[PDB]
Image (tube, helix red, strand yellow):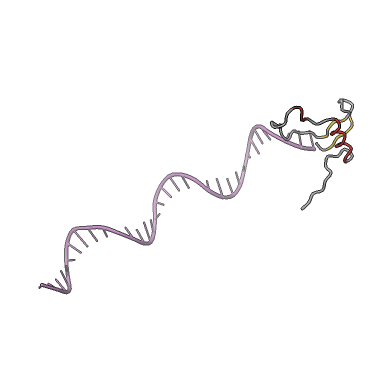
Length: 57
DNA sequence: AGACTTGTACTGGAACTCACGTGAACGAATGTTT
């Protein structure tokens, strides 16, 4: 997703911008899902934008 | 916005075919030897 933005249609209080599926993980169990704490940490890490680090070459 | 599906056009390689070249083999004539 491009970023995480506030919303009122979802329980987490936030929704993704431009979401798309990259892979249906057949190796991850259901209990390995993200947690609200991790989502809050990711949201606060870079002001909601999911692109933080710098391209290198 | 983004991602996939469908339609059009193009280019390169596979396959097939013909032309040309090279290699080996041979019956008959001629020359040489006995």
